[PDB]
Amino acid sequence: HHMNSMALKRINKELSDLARDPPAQCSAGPVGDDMFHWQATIMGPNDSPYQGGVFFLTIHFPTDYPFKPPKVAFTTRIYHPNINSNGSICLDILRSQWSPALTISKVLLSICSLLCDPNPDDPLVPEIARIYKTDRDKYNRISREWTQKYAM
Amino acid sequence: IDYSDAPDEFRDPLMDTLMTDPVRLPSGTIMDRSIILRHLLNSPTDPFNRQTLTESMLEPVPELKEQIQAWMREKQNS
Picture (tube, helix red, strand yellow):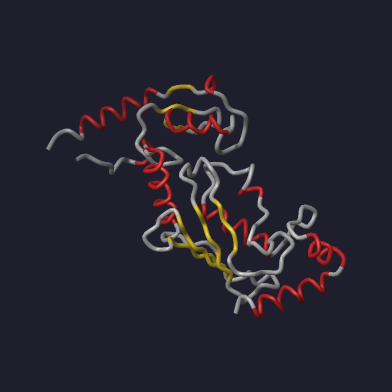
């Protein structure tokens, strides 16, 4: 389609702009050959319990990109109230709140600034959300316990 | 053959294509009518300030168009 070649042309620039400018602790590239399929990596913020661990993501670009938000989620297990066993992430930016002006580079940051501060009033994993609220020490400990065995 | 090479500016803010019918959103942002129109099918909002936006609110920008056309004409020699 024409809306295909276009979406692609955009995707390309985004990638060229992550070379002329890599986001903080964030890295992303096409899974080779396929352009609408990227993997991302995150170095676990130093203001988080995930400090040290490397977390992999998969980015699947809609053919209607950037008019429709890119599907993205973790492959690496991670202890967080807004990320579940599947790998799903809870960002409005990635649902009804996505603007065509938004870019991958931007999204990764939005994700990092989430690993540092989670939103527990709208949680993907209630059990954890309650631990964050009630007993932080617990949370941080556990988050690291997972970052330890899963992300390293 | 042909290509661009286009001096930004002419280029669309979103897709970075060459424009063929520049319009200015209330935002003050200049977009190619074709691109912006496609956005308005999903959500009636400026893709930047996220304010409400309809076709009606799109004012054409001829000054730029001629600038582009003339440019395309110059890119027909040598």
